[PDB]
Image (cartoon, rainbow, N blue to C red):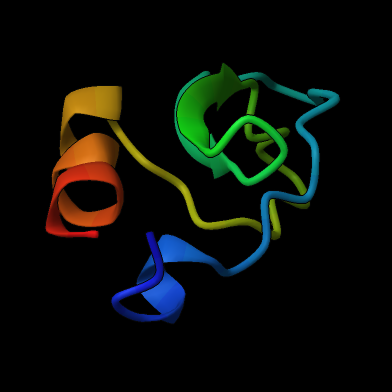
Length: 61
């Protein structure tokens, strides 16, 4: 669960200014969940889908 920093990076949080809603890999649950991404200040490892996120992070390990 740490092949590369692409399985780490930042999540920021995702309050939302315009809200896009993408996924991010939350390393408190070690799984991909969603977040508004904010839009204007989304400083995180954005993932379009969790199946994409899980692919690299969760399944490539």
